Image (tube, rainbow, N blue to C red):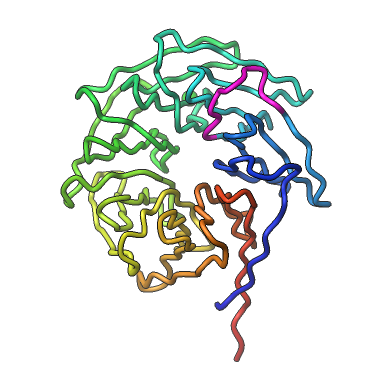
Amino acid sequence: MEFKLQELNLTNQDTGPYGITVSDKGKVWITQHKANMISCINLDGKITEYPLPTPDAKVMCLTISSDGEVWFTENAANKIGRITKKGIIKEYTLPNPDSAPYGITEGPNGDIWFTEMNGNRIGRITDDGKIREYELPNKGSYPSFITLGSDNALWFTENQNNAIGRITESGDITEFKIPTPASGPVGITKGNDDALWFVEIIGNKIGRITTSGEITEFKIPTPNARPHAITAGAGIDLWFTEWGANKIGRLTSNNIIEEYPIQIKSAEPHGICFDGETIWFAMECDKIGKLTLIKDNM
Ligand SMILES: [Cl-]
């Protein structure tokens, strides 16, 4: 699989596209941290803007819930946002000041779970807007990305505790120290192999952790790649952003890592998602990238 890369333009330039996800019907949703908005791109390529109600909110991550609503984090404004199916945005303020919400995902029973990077907590909010939080055991852990595991627990990275965290719906928190010292785990996601796969921004590795906590690691070919986010592709593929190297990485068959250069000065790729055919990513340079592999012959 060699490839095709297309860039798409958002409604404005320099909007700071950052998080990205795709609905089951193929609509791409993005956060734009400089423009302070969320955008949806339909299949026909038409863009709908959702400007945040709160100015200077530093919108970071987003997720689409089972009921089709879009939930997101406002990192600077200390808020969780929600876009209803009616297009209406509702914001909920976190109880403790300067909690710095960051990663967000749906839990096993439908609540929305998130990390509070500076607050040093995991939060959970119900459909009715009730917020509940779990303090992490060690100060200054900087919990970052979060995802739902195959074991129905939430798995997250602790960027400054060099650990992968697991929290269950009942509040059991377990931490698994990473073997590479001070490795700076950032993105995490569920692999199709039912393990969790993460990136080490400093360790410069892709990590794999089983639901029982067994870790293996794979060195990224490009030095100082500063990998950020990761997502499952088809089968055992994991696709990741090399924010520092301006590349898209792919861990594939036999754990070979392939790298695809993005052909754009200071691209700074951040979020990444896969819609089944196309790998979509957000670049700080202000465009959305679409990467597609060409099938093999004979
Ligand atoms: Cl839940």
* Quadrant of residue 144 within the rendered picture: top left
Q: How many marks?
A: 0
- Identify the residue at horizontal 29%, vertical 58% (top origin): 205
Residue 235: image location, x then y, percent: 50, 63
**Where 131 sits versus 222, above or below?**
above
Residue found at the very far bottom of the displayed protein: 298
On the rendered structure, is 124 left or right of 43?
Answer: left
**Quarter of the C terminus within the rendering:** bottom right
Whether residue 231 is in magenta: the answer is no
**Where 84 sits versus 46, above or below?**
above
On the rendered structure, is 70 left or right of 181?
Answer: right
- Identify the residue at horizontal 19%, vertical 24% (top origin): 138
* Quadrant of residue 47 within the rendered picture: top right
Whether residue 59 is in magenta: the answer is yes
Residue 191: image location, x then y, percent: 43, 53
- Identify the residue at horizontal 27%, vertical 44% (top origin): 184
Residue 181: image location, x then y, percent: 16, 48
**Quarter of the N terminus within the rendering:** bottom right
**Where 68 sits versus 121, above or below?**
below
Span highlighted in magenta in the image: 51-61
Residue 7: image location, x then y, percent: 67, 60
Magenta span: chief secondary structure: loop
On the rendered structure, is 241 left or right of 89?
Answer: left
29, 84: nearer the viewer? 29
